[PDB]
Length: 7
Length: 7
Length: 7
Image 1 (cartoon, rainbow over the protein chains, first blue to last red):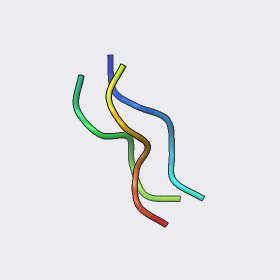
Image 2: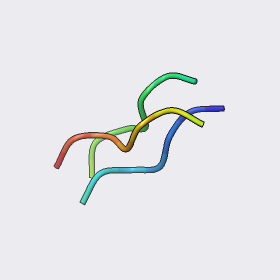
Image 3: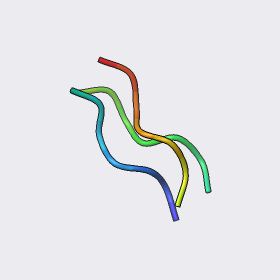
Protein backbone atom coordinates (compact mmCIF):
# COMPACT_ATOMS: atom_id res chain seq x y z
CA UNK A 1 0.00 0.00 0.00
CA UNK A 2 1.03 3.67 -0.36
CA UNK A 3 3.05 5.19 2.46
CA UNK A 4 1.75 7.76 4.93
CA UNK A 5 1.44 11.54 4.22
CA UNK A 6 4.52 13.66 4.74
CA UNK A 7 4.88 16.16 7.58
CA UNK B 1 4.22 0.37 -2.19
CA UNK B 2 4.43 3.83 -3.68
CA UNK B 3 5.34 6.92 -1.61
CA UNK B 4 2.59 8.64 0.39
CA UNK B 5 1.26 12.09 -0.64
CA UNK B 6 2.65 15.44 0.38
CA UNK B 7 1.94 16.75 3.86
CA UNK C 1 3.84 0.06 2.71
CA UNK C 2 5.82 2.68 0.81
CA UNK C 3 7.84 5.54 2.31
CA UNK C 4 6.27 8.69 3.72
CA UNK C 5 5.40 11.49 1.34
CA UNK C 6 7.40 14.76 1.18
CA UNK C 7 6.85 17.76 3.47
